[PDB]
Image 1 (cartoon, rainbow, N blue to C red):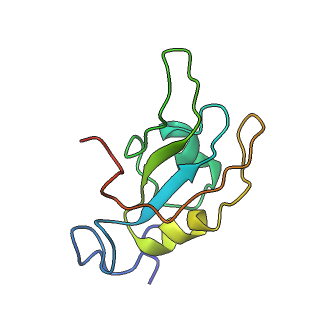
Image 2 (tube, rainbow, N blue to C red):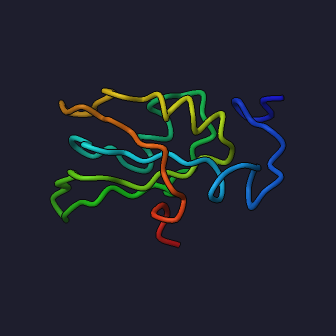
Length: 105
């Protein structure tokens, strides 16, 4: 078990029983809960640098709900429990993503 951080088998499109990978979704997110941040924020997760994208502006007005790709569910879940894990100061109420929403490439 836990090959990377908490990794499973990586047997689906990237681990089994997932939309694709490891569904995590930043929601109600404050200031710049984004690629590199999310990756190392909950250090210990196989969070892909930039399988994440906050609905932002050029300024970086992250708000509604953002995309987060985790190579396996466990990793994904360590962050699907990430409710109220701000950056800046707003309840990061993460959702169990649909990888569908998630990424943009």
